[PDB]
Amino acid sequence: PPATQISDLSKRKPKTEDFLTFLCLRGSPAL
Amino acid sequence: DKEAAFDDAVEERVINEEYKIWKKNTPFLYDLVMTHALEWPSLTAQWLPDVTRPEGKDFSIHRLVLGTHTSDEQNHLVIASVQLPNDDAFGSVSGKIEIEIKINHEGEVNRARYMPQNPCIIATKTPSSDVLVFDYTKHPSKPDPSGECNPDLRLRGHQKEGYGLSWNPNLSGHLLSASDDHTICLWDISAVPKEGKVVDAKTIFTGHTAVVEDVSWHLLHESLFGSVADDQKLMIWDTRSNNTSKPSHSVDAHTAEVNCLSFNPYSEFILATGSADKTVALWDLRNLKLKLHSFESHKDEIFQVQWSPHNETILASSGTDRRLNVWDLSKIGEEQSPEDAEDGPPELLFIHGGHTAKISDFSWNPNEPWVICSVSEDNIMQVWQMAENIYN
Amino acid sequence: SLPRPHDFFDAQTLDAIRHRAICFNLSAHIESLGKGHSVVFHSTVIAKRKEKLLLHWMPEDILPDVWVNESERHQLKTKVVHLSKLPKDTALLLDPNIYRTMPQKRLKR
Amino acid sequence: QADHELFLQAFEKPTQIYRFLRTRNLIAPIFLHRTLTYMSHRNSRTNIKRKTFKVDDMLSKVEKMKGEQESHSHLQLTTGFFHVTLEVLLVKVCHKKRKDVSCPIRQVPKKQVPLNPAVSSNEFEHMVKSYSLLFRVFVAQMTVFDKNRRLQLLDGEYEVAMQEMFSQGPTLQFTLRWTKLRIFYQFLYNNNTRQQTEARDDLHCPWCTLNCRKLYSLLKHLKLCHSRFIFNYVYHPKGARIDVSINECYDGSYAGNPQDIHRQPGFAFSRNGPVKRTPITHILVCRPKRTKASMSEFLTYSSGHNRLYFHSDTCLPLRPQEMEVDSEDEKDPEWLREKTITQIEEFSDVNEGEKEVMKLWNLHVMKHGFIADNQMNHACMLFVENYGQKIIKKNLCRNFMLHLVSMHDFNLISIMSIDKAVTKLREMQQK
């Protein structure tokens, strides 16, 4: 389960306080 | 406000992106899609009935009566020729939307409704209080670099600018116009003395308190015609009523300002009225009070509604929303899949989104089944045909 | 190669869109709780109908307040509604650029 | 590293644009996706357009009017507030006309409520969209009818809470009554930084959140609608692997009037009034084949001016009004005339009047561009038709005669031509 495309997009367009944390707050950059 | 300007800029960027996306999907949405950028924006469009089919050629030639909207230059009454691919196959045939005639016109043309019993005579609505009934055959092909030449007819019965222009089909001539002076004036024309300089109003109608946005004749009876105004009251006037103030019917028919109106070519009772309430509502002349299904998918004013002449259950609407929506009246109330419900109402059949500005006017070509010419304020004229798969 | 066509969006419009998206994701939870296609509104009891309860949802001026019983209120304290089914009259308030009449101006018709 | 940041930004720009477009299109669609041929999975309903529309009135009358059910039907109001006289006003919000920006509200109305211990008329009747009641003590607003005229404000005990400027805050109590297919996305930038994902909802557009029930439909939707990327299907042993990269070309510049692409801020994209533009004709769809759907697919014409032109001299945008004339390239550029004058006047072995007549002749020749010997004859006459007054004022008539003699000695012109030119010069002095 290498993340999800919708989750990656939501980690792409917002990258601020309203980032929903979760796996996006985890090691999303650099795989 | 500065916020309004920023929102307008963002909306311009979004409109450009949406147009690019639509043009990417144009092959999969239309069978014919021809976009022409007119030199001057046009506020009117009406295909001429005459069609020429050259033998041995893969196309056909139709005539479009376009107006002109110049900032300060000399306005014209353009008549152009459009080449359509006919039935099979064109790749490159040089000029396809070239003009044919150009008659000088004082002020921008608001309407270009040709006389049906004689397509030679074409009327026009000027920003002034007088309407001019041109004759493009009589006038020179090239424009004379002078003032607005004698239009062979100049009817003056209004007090301010107008937008409605209806030609009686059942009676030759009989150009009825409704203006912002809350008056719908009717000019007999036709059987009038020659040497046309001024034509007084045969009868003037004052029954709409607000500015009458548009007016149309009944397509079967010569003594009936509907008028719609900004007071949210669509009235069906009956001539020879011994009274020019009280309409035969005075249905409110809407809440906001009601702009356009068009009778059904086939049915003798069905008429549609688009309004500023973002609603195009069908109507039946059999019972005025009751309202039929109200097509509701626009996000702005509905400036023009025109029934298809090749179908009795097809109607198209357009306006400030910059979208041209085609409605199938026989599809009203059909059960839809959740995806179909998400896309839109079952009544709605097609949404044309190739315009980056308000559609000034649109019209169907009588000589072709499902092709529409729509002109926007962006000085863009588009002759487009909906894809065959949409309507079987 | 072919020249770069100078993308029209640029950065200012992109910055405004990013701000609007951040506000939308913080308000309606479209990305997280809306499954990417819905607005997750949270209701709040305002009045009690002792004859139901009137509830107003967190994004104001989007959906009208409705009367729900106490069990119904507990069941539907939070409502998720798809953007397609949003009321067309007030759906435009979710973003300034959801639909803006480009020629506001004047004159015209 | 900075490579990942660059990749994130380069993918975030189109991703943000398409996410905003997704949040916008579901309420304001560019087109019906059910009308797209590649999206034929939707619109799950055939064409039964064979029934006349003249019976719609009867059908609607039987369905609605014949089986009409009363939606509803004075109002009775009364308990106490919690935390003082309060005002109860009936607000009627009117329909949004074109003139009005927002929906107008007319407030048609006091009672001495206890400091934290009414019979209404038939004002309802439809210019007003809905009827609402506003209470101010400390404010509270409640609607009595919905959009469909739904009967709100139920009769009975009502503890309508109030917002400062039931609930824990200041609340008011009142009595109301009457009277499988796993899809993998491998984002690639510069072929060195890759992010491999997998769609949470299979056969769903990651950007548009659109339900493309078929893999071919989804791939075509990605390639068409989200054109800012390039989607190279590569297939997967389990499902489908759709590699995604940023579309390098993506010609997505301004598509409107080319003039606006260079106007000063405050006038670009003004849309305030009509603007002239050069005519152009485009054909996008003429007669498409409409071939059968197949995955093998994943292995224009314009007439007229279709750009913005610029002046060769100033490199400034060329307006459509300045197009039909002003070719801006003429025989004698001003710099050439100035250089000729300077070169003539820069000679050492020449008289002042000789230099003046030489410069006048050169300027005249450049202005008229004689290339033929015989025309030279008439050229001399043209000289006295344009430079005769200037030569006379300069008092270089003798030098002009000397130049004519030299030119005749160089062939072209003639003795008769010399006499005619001199006589024409004399007539100028007598005048």
Image (cartoon, coloured by chain):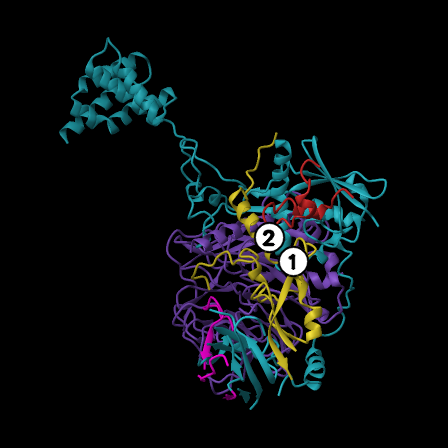
Chain colours: A red, B purple, C yellow, D cyan
- Quadrant hosting residue A25: top right
Relative side of D409 to D169, left or right: left
Residue position for label 1:
D26
Image coordinates for residue D133, horizontal then vertical, percent: 51, 78
The single residue placed furthest to the left in the displayed view is D430
Relative side of D408 to D227, left or right: left
Q: Residues within 10 Å of mark 2 (few under 14, many from 20)?
A: many
Which three-letter amino acid code belongs to the residue tagged 2?
Val
Secondary-structure class at tag 2:
strand
What is the count of numbered marks? 2
What's drawn in magenta, residue-wise? D95-122
Image coordinates for residue D274, horizontal then vertical, percent: 45, 53
Residue position for label 2:
B82
The single residue placed furthest to the bottom in the displayed view is D179
Secondary structure mostly taken by the magenta-highlighted segment of the chain = loop
Is residue D303 among the parts visible in the rendering? yes
Which residue is depicted at the point 73% across and 62% down? B340
Q: Is residue B100 above or below residue D107?
A: above
The single residue placed furthest to the right in the displayed view is D237
Which residue is depicted at the point 70% across and 31% down? D191
Q: Is residue D8 above or below residue C18?
A: above
Which residue is depicted at the point 36% across and 26% down? D332
Image coordinates for residue D403, horizontal then vertical, percent: 25, 16
The single residue placed furthest to the front in the displayed view is D117
Relative side of D187 to D250, left or right: right
Q: Residues within 10 Å of mark 1 (few under 14, many from 20)?
A: many
Image coordinates for residue D369, horizontal then vertical, percent: 36, 25
Magenta stretch contains residue D113: yes
Which three-letter amino acid code belongs to the residue tagged 1?
Leu
Is residue B366 among the parts visible in the rendering? no
Secondary-structure class at tag 1:
loop
